[PDB]
Length: 49
Length: 192
Length: 47
Length: 51
Image (cartoon, rainbow over all chains, first blue to last red; front, side, top):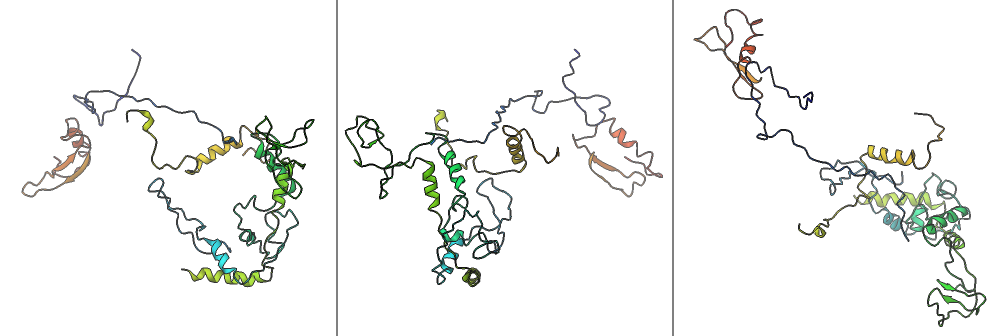
């Protein structure tokens, strides 16, 4: 309801009757997480001894 | 141009990131230092310049040579480090002292230098006590060393003492260098 | 594997050497040049 | 459309069949085959009208 989750595009003007068949076989978008590590801003690189 | 003198080759770097791009690179892998060594045969008795000035890294444009050669001074001393190999401005060693010990210990005493120059290394006196020195451990004493007396060199003095002994170098006398370099090429063109 | 302690690695050039793609070098230098040290007093220009 | 060729066939003058393939599916859909047949009516020529 007022959400507009996803827009799609037909190739060319589907005209009379249309069918969309999900290519992965009956699954909509699927997601995967990413881990974006902390950028460690430093190069003193002190060493013991 | 008495370095280089050959070609870029190509540096594949294929052992890392296969299908890495080939980058033309000045050729530093010839074992140059040998050519110099063998070519030098017969020009020896290169005298001892003693330096005498905290000459910056290049005195080549003053003393023997002087096409700003910046080496044949290197190959002299078989210098591993072109930076700290040559002697440095007196303050530099001091400056070099801190960064060495800055992490641990602060300023210290490296050895106590008996007269006649017998170093000791972690040997410690006790004032207001017997006058005989002890190691930095076995605080029960019982195991004295060097019943005599001497004077510690702390740290700064050592670095000075250590880099200042690094001023003597060979020369090739400003006479041979032209005749010498005229040979040093010949060996190079020889092997190919 | 099963126990995670068996991962180790094959012959591995550490991240210490590797070497630059260019612009990542531009990134690390700027952060070392502008930041943590100067907060520019530079007399050259804005550009 | 992808991969078109047009071939004229003697003994049937006046047609000049064209063969078109979709970049998506296999057969050409209606209101597409119809729409390809237009825009060639503005040009065409002559007798010999498309197929």
